[PDB]
Image (cartoon, coloured by chain):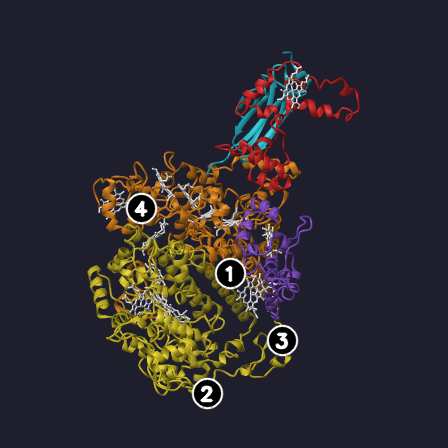
Chain colours: A cyan, B orange, C yellow, D purple, E red
């Protein structure tokens, strides 16, 4: 029997615009965002802590409980202070 | 019907005081020096905490094969010598043990490429240093690690612990002489230890493993009418009517793709083919003896998951509300038992229990603790033992009242839970169900009435009643561990004598389960329990 | 659930004092005047020693047909006259009793050449002089003498003697009105008297006879859970799962060529198709109520033979040791019963048994012998009867203590023997097995305690307890043989009134059996037993 | 009807599997469909009793046959035995829940003997 | 996914008709299904933006291509032109409702040009 892993999308926003180069921590996994501002994680069932950090000093946190074969998109806005020139 | 003492050659008739192990016929089995189990026979000691008091027979070697067989200090002698190739195994046994080879040949293990899984893969090459393959042998990474690990996911009361906890540390088994409780070794060790369960050796057919009846050889009878409840329920009616119709039941299909007209044990409990059989269970309730409202908001996810299984053939509402009825039937059951246990508890606090625990033959520990005393609910003088320590819960060596309580909760109540869970309406009512608990309550009342009427008379007449000798000792009672421990190790208990850590000590509840409870409890605002 | 006294027309309600054979409804069966069995109804007397006291029903004519049907004095009337050819039997019955002809036409008998074994061959040509064919009719030299002789090789407690001994000299059947024990006639006579057993008339298919379920119709229930033990065991699990799979169970094969995945009753007991079903039995132990260590060196050769049967699908060691476990369970069971019996025996010796045998209704014999008295072990004033004479072993017309003792050895103990023998671990433990005896031991002790406490109180207060009237007489009790003998033949017993030689007088153990035992006792140096 | 089948074929697969096997689905000129027994409005669904099956247009024969039964028959096992069941009334529900599930069926639901 | 399709095939037929025609439904080893774009939890459904389509595992190429656009392109027509639209901000909503519906699409929703 194969336990189908959950798929978690995490989007980092700064009042609408995607944050480039933000680091998203979900469980033990780390992803540094591209132009999307979106990281996709494939995770085994369980409860996880999502944390989005960006070099400006802004952070967003959300705790998520994932079942078997769950698909969840998470959208976290870090405010206007997370918007940096170029 | 008589105890026939004629016809049978006279020369074989057994006479008083003659050994029982002579093989002479003793009428009704009377007047014979109880010789006890062959302590000289080449065998292995049981593993575990109570190893020192575990009296074993030779037969017991096969049932925990890792410790009780495969060791060079314990391996049974075999007449056949030499180290053989697979072709040799098959050639010789095909006539010596013909059934085994017919089986093995049918099995896929024999056809496996490039190399087959042959006798020697599971047993070895040296016919002197033969091994017996345990669950671990099947569950190698190279082989069947998946199913092994799945099965091991099981907690207490599962196929993962049914030997190492429930049997290796089985109160009665330890207390009594083996043979009394032989069937217990043969039944409990299997699922955890021998992967020939459900899919029988040496054929190992998943097709036959996927059949409901496979589960009946253990899940039946006095303290778990699982089979009987399923069988007689409408699911079992459907099953029996249809099970050989291929348009209704195709056993070749993997459970994942299984589209039966009605459900099988495996369809619900081994959903997806998951070898953890307990994977969908809500909470462990000591066989259904302990009580819980499974419909309650706390277990909402776990009961919803159940509704997702029934969903395949019923509307969510139908199942949801049916599984609710079970909960009600479970709650109304424990109501009855509380009144039953009250009547029983009263006779102990009042002290007019006939007899008191202190007068009975000492329990497996050597202590005189009350039978029905649940440690985490009872403490005081009249109960006995240290704080929070339970008695030896049993139906034997005790008052009728103590007996009819155990019976009521440990048999009849478990017919209401499993009866209602499986759709057998009679198992939860007329057939020793609710109406059985009714019957026993009446029987417990009357058996208190009598114990009071007498003990009141003996006070007003001034006789001090002496508990009879048969409560203390007796031919059987004397063979038990209690009397041994009292005599031989006077200032200690079995727990004192067996200090080493138990199964509970090493094996914990999964983290993800503890987390879920805490989350759901704070979610609803209900406080926790004590130690 | 109520005793419904409505809806059904009143005209048909029976009122107090009215005959029970009127056909009127008596609520809960109360208030009716017992008219007894129709003694004017054309029927046969039963054969054997106790013919005079054997009350019979018309239906019994079929069950021992040579004596009860085939004699001119007894043969029942028939509305159809004439002597007929076979063609005529078939043509007429094809409509009159369709199923019989359907079965006959399927049978090999109908197809036989040069002449078929037709209705007339088994029943006769003259419709006014019809006969019912017994085992003797089938077992003629010209026909099936082989199977008749095979079956006839059986000793006491076999298919050879189950009518002539067990049933014809059945204490309870003789004692009671007929109908009370009607089922006993219908069950017991069949194997010995009628060869439509196992292979049903009129099809007589050996293929259906090879199925395990054939045995269940008789080999089940309270005093021999043969079927239940087999069925729920892993052999029975394998059977139920595979029985309709021709690749696993081929019932068209003869038993000599049987290559099943798992065993059938026939596979083990009718090895090679031998009709002596007891052929492989080690020693007769009175349904397993009597105790023997079958694994003892005395029975080595006989146990070895059993291992030879298991050998087919298991290692000798595995089978030997498993059957050794059975032996241990059997010995440990009798240990318990010895303790149980002691409690009951002590009540009798101390004279505090409530009541003593003298205050019970007279037994079938017309005597007041203790129920549990075994003539070979018990002798004294308290037990009653002559030296060596046993009591009427029963669950009826006795004390609770006597009853529970009967139940413990006569029911629960047999579940342990049969359970362990057939691989039903729960039958030997939880399901009224070992733990059944445990529960009954408690029940016996409690009943002993209460009786002793009352006797002590009555002594001190100066009451001499007069045993109640219902122990002596009652509506049912009055209809028994006991009261009739005491009243009508005051000085004598049933043995006096039936002086003819019994089955045991004319039937002895085979020479080879005595020869084997004597040889083995000398070989091992064990003392021979007494009468 | 198409919509009942399509949706339930996934939502409650077993029911549709059973329905498709049934003669009801194959009946002409019009099938006895989910809607025929349950209704069209999902907010006003109904559960079909023996009365629904036993309509003159359908299976009046079997309904009338069963209804010929007296006391203690399939005709009265709900209306009398269960509806006026002393113990069931006396006790909390659940104590005798099984009695409701067992007794009502023969009289009230024709999915008895021949399963839905 | 089976459940999304079955239920919506009746509830919102046109969406399922379109989906079944799409390459997404036929994709192997696993299809890009309703759940892939919208989520599994019906209480936690999401609407997939250009960022969702433009994930590295999927259509990063097209996302990056579009994103190369400067001011007045499909890359900025929402974020600049519409989000900082003087008139839209100035007026009651509805006065310029059409501006939201038109401007956001190219940048935010890849159902543009190739319809969902
Ligand atoms: C010991 C721990 C075990 C091992 C190793 C295996 N099993 Fe079983 N098993 C059971 C069933 C009903 C099936 C069919 C499952 C399905 O339809 O999906 C199986 C199947 C297997 C298989 C085949 C692998 C596969 O699914 O493709 C293997 C290799 C296997 N099992 C190994 C039932 C049971 C069972 C009854 C409760 C027990 C105790 C075990 N299985 C134990 C083992
Ligand atoms: C005997 C060899 C068994 C067979 C065959 C099957 N099971 Fe079992 N099961 C067995 C034991 C001894 C135990 C637990 C004993 C204990 O430690 O308490 C179990 C446990 C279960 C459970 C869990 C029950 C609970 O936790 O309260 C389930 C759900 C279960 N078993 C189901 C099950 C099914 C469906 C089987 C057939 C495929 C099956 N079991 C086989 C012993 C045996
Ligand atoms: C072949 C036709 C058999 C004969 C003859 C006997 N047994 Fe058997 N037995 C057979 C099978 C196919 C199985 C199932 C194996 C499995 O994996 O479960 C069994 C099972 C048993 C068992 C229980 C299984 C176990 O604990 O190992 C026992 C105890 C057992 N068999 C013993 C036994 C004895 C004593 C027999 C002779 C009287 C016997 N079996 C006959 C196949 C066959
Ligand atoms: C689905 C329709 C089922 C089938 C088929 C069988 N059982 Fe079951 N079982 C089912 C439910 C809904 C429950 C109650 C779960 C709950 O906690 O609410 C059970 C219960 C059991 C248990 C006890 C599990 C526990 O206490 O944790 C056991 C041991 C069990 N069932 C075994 C079992 C067996 C052997 C079956 C085949 C005959 C069987 N079940 C059928 C649902 C279903
Ligand atoms: C008439 C012949 C029916 C048709 C056509 C369908 N069903 Fe039915 N259904 C029928 C009966 C007699 C019953 C029992 C009603 C009761 O009171 O118990 C049912 C029951 C259901 C149920 C609920 C019971 C359950 O098993 O969950 C559902 C959800 C249901 N039926 C759905 C259903 C669907 C989707 C159908 C179309 C394929 C359908 N039924 C056909 C009688 C009849
Ligand atoms: C009823 C008609 C029976 C059928 C069918 C079968 N058996 Fe039987 N069996 C029956 C009786 C009444 C008795 C003995 C009664 C007595 O006189 O004590 C027996 C005996 C046996 C025995 C011997 C038991 C003993 O204690 O020695 C065996 C081993 C036995 N029967 C097995 C058996 C089998 C395997 C059958 C199916 C093929 C079978 N019996 C059919 C009654 C009936
Ligand atoms: C059940 C315990 C049986 C009783 C009682 C009798 N028979 Fe039977 N018979 C039985 C079986 C299981 C079989 C098949 C055995 C086999 O060899 O495979 C038979 C077979 C016969 C046959 C066919 C003989 C042959 O060619 O193999 C005959 C003619 C026969 N039996 C006759 C017979 C008679 C006359 C009986 C009464 C005394 C009788 N049988 C009893 C099972 C049982
Ligand atoms: C082989 C594996 C067996 C099958 C299949 C059945 N039984 Fe058996 N039976 C078997 C053994 C090894 C024994 C013990 C014999 C001994 O004394 O060692 C028995 C016992 C009986 C008995 C009692 C016989 C006696 O001598 O007292 C009976 C009456 C009996 N078995 C009947 C029986 C029936 C009816 C079966 C089918 C359901 C059956 N047995 C299966 C071995 C095997
Ligand atoms: C449960 C759903 C049942 C099924 C399936 C069958 N029967 Fe039934 N039957 C049932 C009940 C609750 C009752 C009567 C209860 C009462 O009001 O007293 C009956 C009644 C009968 C009767 C009449 C009994 C009497 O005392 O007159 C018969 C003869 C009968 N049932 C037979 C029967 C048969 C042959 C069935 C299968 C086809 C059958 N019933 C199914 C409950 C249920
Ligand atoms: C509405 C949803 C549009 C569709 C469909 C297409 N285009 Fe577009 N386009 C749209 C907007 C709102 C804008 C820019 C708004 C702004 O921020 O100023 C554009 C931009 C272009 C441009 C660039 C114009 C410029 O001044 O540089 C081009 C060349 C263009 N669009 C072309 C184009 C083509 C060829 C399309 C069909 C395939 C197309 N667009 C679709 C709005 C929308
Ligand atoms: C000759 C015949 C062989 C050969 C070449 C092999 N085996 Fe055996 N085996 C044989 C016999 C006669 C017996 C039974 C001995 C007895 O009890 O009387 C066995 C036994 C086994 C066993 C069972 C051991 C036990 O019960 O504890 C096993 C597991 C076994 N044999 C396996 C085996 C393997 C793997 C072989 C090939 C390497 C092999 N045998 C060869 C007879 C013979
Ligand atoms: C490794 C080598 C092993 C071991 C130690 C065991 N088995 Fe298996 N088994 C193995 C193979 C290569 C196969 C063929 C199918 C496959 O590649 O998965 C099997 C087959 C089975 C099956 C399925 C049989 C069928 O489909 O008809 C079962 C149920 C099975 N094996 C069980 C099993 C058990 C219980 C074992 C220990 C006693 C065991 N196996 C050992 C490879 C290996
Ligand atoms: C019910 C009773 C019964 C009705 C009353 C009568 C008269 C008998 C007779 C006996 C006797 C006698 C025996 C021998 C044993 C003893 O201890 O006295 C008893 C055996 C018995 C077996 C044999 C089981 C074994 O030996 O292992 C079987 C198969 C019996 C079954 C019938 C039964 C058919 C369903 C019914 C009714 C009775 N018996 Fe019996 N009998 N029987 N029995
Ligand atoms: C369990 C009980 C129950 C739960 C409490 C209720 C209320 C009933 C009701 C009755 C009544 C009333 C009858 C009529 C007889 C009488 O003596 O009062 C009773 C009949 C009954 C039968 C008929 C058998 C016959 O007539 O030969 C059947 C088949 C019953 C079975 C159900 C059952 C399903 C498994 C459960 C649960 C109960 N009964 Fe009953 N009932 N019943 N019964």
Question: Gap between marks 1 and 3, in whole Å?
Answer: 58 Å
| Residue B277 seen | no
User: Which chain is home to disc 3?
Assistant: C
Asked if disc 3 is less than 8 Å from ligand 9, the answer is no
Q: Position of residue C109 (x, y in %)?
A: 31, 72
Q: Position of residue B409 (x, y in %)?
A: 54, 54
Residue C8, label in figure: 3
Q: Nearer the viewer, mark 2 or mark 4?
A: 4
Q: Residue furthest front?
A: D29
Is disc 2 surrounded by few (<14), some (14 to 19) or many (20+) residues within 10 Å?
Answer: few
Residue that carries the numbered disc 1 in the rendered image: B466
User: Which chain is home to disc 4?
Assistant: B
Residue in the foreground of this view, choosing between C196 and B362: C196
Q: What SS does tag 1 mark?
A: loop
Question: Gap between marks 3 and 4, in whole Å?
Answer: 65 Å
Q: Residue at x 52, y 79 (%)?
A: C474
Residue C40, label in figure: 2
Q: Is residue C16 above or below residue B142?
A: below
Q: Residue furthest top?
A: A86
Q: Nearer the viewer, mark 3 or mark 2?
A: 3
Q: Nearer the viewer, mark 1 or mark 3?
A: 3
Q: Is residue D106 left or right of residue C336?
A: right
Q: Is residue C463 left or right of residue B108?
A: right
Residue that carries the numbered disc 4 in the rendered image: B104
The quadrant in which the N terminus of chain B is found is bottom left
| Residue B274 seen | yes
């Amino acid at each position: 029997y194969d336990v189908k892993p959950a798929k978690l999308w995490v989007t980092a926003i700064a009042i609408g615009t995607p944050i480039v180069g933000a680091e998203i921590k979900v469980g033990d996994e780390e992803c540094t965002t591209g132009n999307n501002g979106t990281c996709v994680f494939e995770l085994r069932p369980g409860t996880y802590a999502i944390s989005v950090h960006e070099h400006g000093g802004q952070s967003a946190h959300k705790e998520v409980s994932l079942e078997e074969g769950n698909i969840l998109f998470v959208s976290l806005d870090l405010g206007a202070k997370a918007r940096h020139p170029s | 019907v008589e105890i026939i003492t004629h016809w049978v050659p006279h020369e074989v008739y057994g006479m008083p005081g003659e050994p029982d192990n002579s093989g002479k016929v003793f009428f009704s089995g009377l007047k014979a020096k109880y010789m006890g189990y062959p302590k000289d026979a080449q065998r292995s000691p049981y593993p575990g905490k109570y190893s020192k008091f575990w009296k074993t027979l030779p037969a017991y070697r096969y049932y925990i094969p890792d410790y009780m067989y495969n060791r060079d200090e314990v391996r049974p002698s075999n007449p056949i010598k030499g180290t053989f190739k697979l072709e040799q195994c098959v050639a010789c046994h095909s006539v010596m043990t013909p059934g085994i080879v017919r089986d093995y040949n049918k099995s896929a293990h024999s056809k496996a490429e490039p190399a087959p899984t042959g006798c020697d893969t599971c047993h070895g090459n040296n016919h002197q240093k033969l091994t017996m393959p345990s669950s671990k042998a099947c569950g190698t990474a190279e082989c069947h690690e998946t199913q092994y690990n799945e099965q091991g996911q099981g907690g207490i009361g599962s196929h993962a612990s049914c030997s190492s906890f429930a049997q290796v540390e089985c109160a009665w088994s330890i207390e009594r002489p083996p043979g009394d409780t032989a069937g217990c070794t043969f039944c409990h060790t299997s699922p955890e230890e021998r992967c020939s369960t459900c899919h029988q050796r040496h054929q190992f057919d998943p097709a036959v493993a996927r059949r409901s009846e496979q589960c009946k050889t253990c899940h039946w009878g006095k303290d778990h009418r699982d089979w009987e409840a399923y069988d007689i329920g409408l699911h079992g009616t459907v099953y029996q009517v249809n099970k050989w119709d291929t348009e209704q039941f195709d056993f070749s299909k993997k459970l994942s793709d299984a589209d039966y007209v009605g459900p099988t044990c495996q369809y619900c409990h081994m959903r997806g083919g998951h070898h953890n059989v307990q994977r969908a269970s809500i909470v462990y309730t000591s066989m259904g003896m302990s009580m819980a409202d499974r419909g309650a908001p706390l277990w909402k996810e776990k009961r919803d998951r159940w509704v997702s299984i029934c969903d395949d053939c019923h509307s969510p509402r139908f199942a949801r509300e049916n599984l609710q009825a079970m909960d009600e039937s479970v709650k109304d059951a424990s109501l009855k038992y509380r009144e039953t246990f009250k009547v029983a508890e009263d006779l102990l606090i009042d002290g007019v229990l006939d007899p008191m625990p202190k007068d009975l033959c000492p329990d497996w520990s050597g202590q005189h603790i009350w039978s029905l005393k649940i440690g985490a609910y009872h403490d005081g003088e009249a109960y006995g033992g240290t704080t929070g320590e339970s008695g030896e819960f049993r139906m034997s060596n005790c008052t009728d009242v103590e007996r009819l309580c155990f019976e009521s909760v440990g048999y009849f109540q478990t017919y209401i839970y499993k009866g209602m869970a499986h759709g057998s309406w009679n198992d939860a009512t007329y057939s020793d169900g609710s109406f059985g608990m009714d019957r026993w309550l009446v029987n417990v009342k009357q058996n208190a009435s009598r114990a009071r009427r007498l003990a009141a008379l003996e006070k007003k007449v001034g006789i001090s009643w002496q508990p009879e000798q048969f409560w203390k000792t007796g031919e059987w009672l004397d063979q038990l561990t209690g009397p041994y421990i009292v005599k031989n190790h006077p200032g200690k208990t079995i727990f004192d004598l067996c200090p080493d850590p138990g199964w509970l000590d090493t094996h914990h509840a999964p983290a993800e389960e503890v987390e879920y409870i805490e989350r759901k409890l704070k979610e609803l605002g209900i406080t926790a329990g004590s130690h």
